[PDB]
Length: 184
Image (cartoon, rainbow, N blue to C red; front, side, top):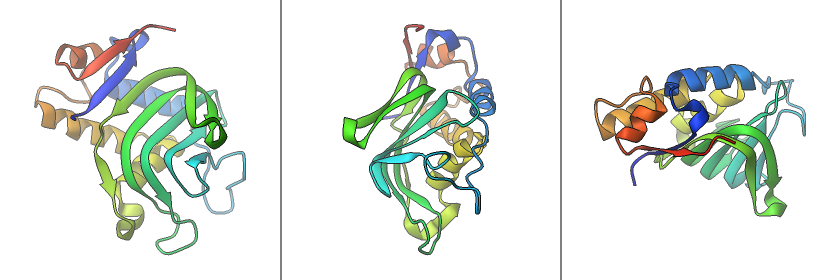
């Protein structure tokens, strides 16, 4: 299945690039870096976990913003290549107010704004932090969605050259790629 995008009608006239740029500024930088990682503050979590899961999810420390990365994800922690998130990234869901976790049978967003699915991204452990999956997710954690933007852009252009991250969600819905959900 090719890339599918779900969006609240609230963002119908926003370009994907503007939405993501503004969302990352709103989520901010959790400062997930050497000497600055604090359990339960800026780590996020895996479902099932502890270091691998079908979901990785993280709440903003600056706001109610949160994201859920979906697929088949793995984190190396201290083992070479250290601090690498790798595996399959199938989806990114962006919104407010993270709920759930491993014990609930999954993370969710109370106010999901936008989701990108069927991303088809797959990065091997041996690529380390140069892997696309790593860069996309760490980008989000650190207030820079450029890697995510770049991957969405490539996927959209591969569906049709008239589609890009500078398309509005409505324009992408006109092409059958994006699908509106009610404004909550």
